[PDB]
Image (cartoon, rainbow over the protein chains, first blue to last red):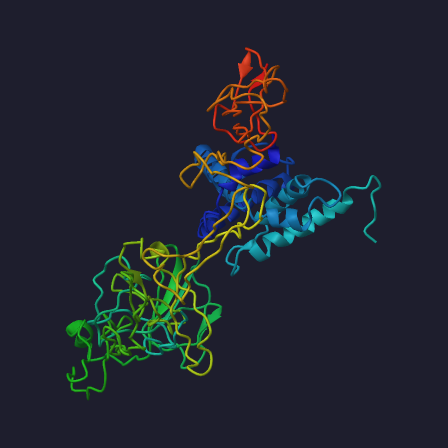
Length: 156
Length: 395
């Protein structure tokens, strides 16, 4: 009779897959960065995006082949994402519900996680365990209090 | 009891458990559960180890030589170093520098390194004409990047069944219990084992696994608790705690004293000297209790008296009442109380008279209650109540 339990209950088993795949992801971390980063640099020179797959990469890339870069590069920043969904409880506990809801104080923390990966930083010297949080707790807070009193408050 | 210090099979730099001639046989508890029988030899190559799977090319890892005598740079970690460094990259990124102690030498004259290979300087033999000082464990292979030799050190110590026996004397009350002293050492691990960079000051522990075997619990009080507690009359003056590691069968008996008008006065008696092995056949502890008023205690049962009910006779029990009436009743007439019951004069008497005929009655007290059929009983016969116990109910 519980979706929080659900979170358990299906991700309490989710692991971190270690931090080795960090570089396996790094390859993709970029690669995606690229694939877009081009494709909107190319939005940005012209056509505001021709909605063309090839333009999805400045360098040439057979449609299916590059279709493998994405999706694979994506599950990279998706599995690791789903993987790094355990310690998050720390932020939940530390911020209980912040006058909101335990869950909303973790789904808003999920807005973090993603806002880690991307600007998580590969070849750094340690996990976002000291950086992922960082976002996390800077993304919740911002919420929380943006969130919740039905009068927005300025932070000042 | 207590945990001993045994500095031997310590060290202050890492390992290699390539030991010699100590022996457990593997026996699983080559582990805690440690056996330590035999080994005046621990051939061990302390070291540095850094299991940090990290991206390729962090700062710089350099094989073919030892980094720096003192804290050296590696790849954004540094080193309370002791020597040559197995450089340790493997799979798209590297994972665990294993530095192993000391001593480069400089193998040029190439034809050297494995030209003698898992043989070190046994202190006593020497290799290419170099004074043989101590155990220079030959680097398994050595010289990549070509010019620089290694045969590392070794370290070794003698540890027998027990390098130092403690006290080693102990007998107990033992009416069959069988207690024993035992100071087994303890062992970092066995050649299944390849050590890494830890305190390393942990390669021995002669604590006490002192046990107590033998069954016969009947006299062997708590065998599967043959298990220690230790107290303090040996604190000073024989200051050494007697270290019985004693067990206990402190049987608990209530005072059972209450002089209840049914339980009564309960007699307490012991035999405690400071301990006959529960005196085979003992006068351990007693509770003699007493029965209400005058009483031919009668048909009264075999001690346990599960049925606390006890047939028994007081002056009042037998109703003792003037039979001016002629000799008319006898050993157990059924008086249900009516008329002409004490013929001429009448009485209230009740239950089962054992006679009304010297003119003084015989009924042990009795009192009837008509009932019906329809019944659900409890009492049957020979049931001296106490009050309000349930008897034969009628639904």
